[PDB]
Amino acid sequence: GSEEIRELVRKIYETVRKENPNVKILIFIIFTSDGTIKVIIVIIADDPNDAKRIVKKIQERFPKLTIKQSRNEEEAEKRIQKELEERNPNAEIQVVRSEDELKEILDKLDEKKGSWSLEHHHHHH
């Protein structure tokens, strides 16, 4: 259930900030046609030589979770999406950067069980 994913991300966000508070994390949540979940963790730092240390921390602490390092801001959200689409052809990929977005995916699973949508993509700065 999505609450277990919502617990897990905090254990990562405390572990990563304990060694460096500057660095950002992206969480990829996969929904397969067979109902299986995958959880991919991506580290974005201002220097990828630091990101590699943080990734190694999560690799030792969570050996059953697959993880990545990234050098550019916002790019990994689309770059890794297409790698994930190529290796999960019968799946949906969602990206999370705060635990409220992990709560929103639980509401979006109900919108996907439904047949409805509202408003438009307005664009802003």
Image: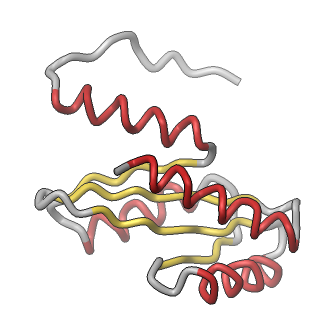
In front here: 121 or 65? 65
Q: Residue at x 56, y 62 (%)?
A: 76
Query: Based on the displayed image, in which of its 4 quarters is residue 81 positioned?
Result: bottom left
Query: Based on the displayed image, in which of its 4 quarters is residue 69 positioned?
Result: bottom right
Q: Residue at x 55, y 60 (%)?
A: 8
In front here: 37 or 82? 37
| Colour logic | secondary structure
Q: How many marks?
A: 0
In front here: 42 or 75? 42
Q: Is residue 60 above or below residue 67?
A: below
In the picture provided, is 94 more to the left or to the right than 46?
Answer: left
Q: Residue at x 15, y 61 (%)?
A: 90
**Percent position (x, y) of residue 33?**
12, 57
**Percent position (x, y) of residue 97?**
61, 48
In the picture provided, is 112 more to the left or to the right than 94?
Answer: left
**Percent position (x, y) of residue 32?**
20, 59
Q: Is residue 16 above or below residue 13?
A: below
In the picture provided, is 62 more to the left or to the right than 94?
Answer: right
Query: Based on the displayed image, in which of its 4 quarters is residue 99 positioned?
Result: top right
**Percent position (x, y) of residue 17?**
82, 63
The quarter of the image holding the C terminus is top right
Q: Residue at x 53, y 38 (%)?
A: 101
